[PDB]
Amino acid sequence: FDCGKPQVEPKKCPGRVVGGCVAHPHSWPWQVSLRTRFGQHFCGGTLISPEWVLTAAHCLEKSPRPSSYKVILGAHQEVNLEPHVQEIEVSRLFLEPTRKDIALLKLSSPAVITDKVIPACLPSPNYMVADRTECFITGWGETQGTFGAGLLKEAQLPVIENKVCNRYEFLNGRVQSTELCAGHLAGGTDSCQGDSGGPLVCFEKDKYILQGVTSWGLGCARPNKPGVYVRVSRFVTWIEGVLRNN
Image 1: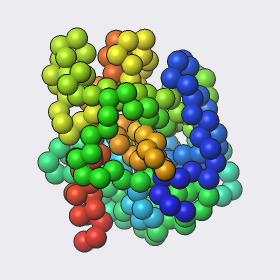
Image 2: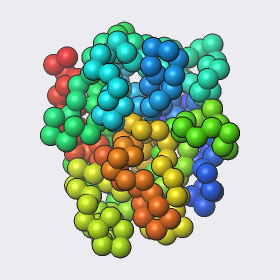
Image 3: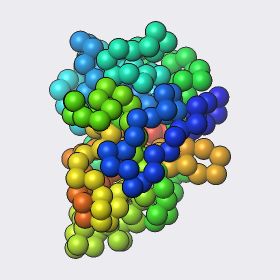
C-alpha cells in the first residue's frame, strides 16, 4: 500500500457541516490513537512509516518514558476496538529540538501494513500548502456525549495562507512559518478539532499528504479565526533524518 492512499474512500465531510462527520471506518489508515498504559485515548498521531508516528510534543508531557505510551492503529472505535486493531508500544520519543512542538514516536515493532493501517505521506521539505487547499483534520476528540462520541471523526478545513492568517484580524502575526493555518476565516468552528497530535492531511494529486500536526496550543479555530497547526513540511528533513539514523 503506497502512503496516503486509503483503501476505503474517505467520505470527505463538506466544510459547511457543523461538527464535521464520522469518518468512513478506516478511511484514514494512518490515524493513530495514542494511549496511556491503561487503555486511555488521549492523543492522535499520524503513522508516517511502519515504525514511526508523528504527534504533538504536548502529547508527551505526562511522561518521559516511551513505555508509558501505546499506539493503537487501524481503529475507528475509541473504546471498543474492532479485533483487528494493532496495539504497539512506543520504544522511543524524539522531540523536535528547534520548536519542540512535535515529536516522533518509534514503535516497539513495525506496524503491519494492511488496508486499514497505511502511513500518510510526508510533504516535500518546505512545501507550502496553497491558500484554500482543502484538507481534513481527523481524530476522536475529548468531548463525550457529543456527536460521534467515541468515533473517528473528520472535518474539512481549507488552508489559510500565513500572510493572510497573520493579519491582525486573525492570528495577528503569531503564526510562524514553521506553522500553518487551517479553518474558515469566518463561520469556522468554535472548538479545538481532531486530537492533540492528530493529522491535518491534504489530498494532492494521487494521495493524502500530512501537511499539519494538530497542536491546540498554537491555536484552535474561533468562528472568525482559523486554527494553527505545525507545518510538517518545515520538519521533514529533521524527521527523515531521525528515521534513517534510528
